[PDB]
Length: 143
Image (cartoon, rainbow, N blue to C red; front, side, top):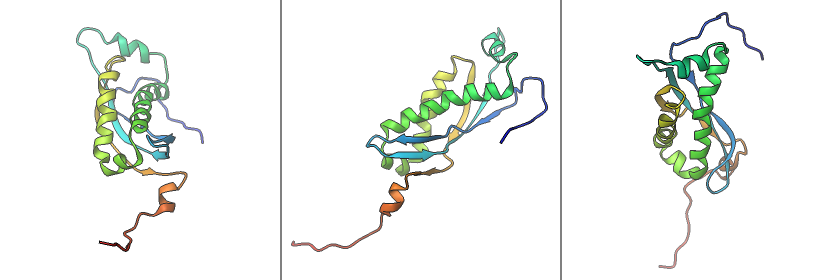
């Protein structure tokens, strides 16, 4: 599946990058699939934005979105590794907050600022959890 969009100029407009990762064994050791969804945009410098401008000048829109997307993406995995399969689902809103909180002060190196970070869908390709199907059960007790 190839892409095709007319445009021979940088697109300052806000860029929508979805930091998704597959086959990322959680803290315990369970590979999960997180789509993730975050928005980003180019930053301006009243002085000189040659740090991001020259870094995007000449390249192709796709390239840019990739570079930026990578920064966030990578982080996700790192934050997903230290986080188990529970902590994640339990408080997803937080998980994303970390990926953005850790990448926020990072993208500032290239010249990009993050707007927001959220989670789209988190499923397990190995269908491990599903198979287990967590359900309320009953059990006997002595006293």
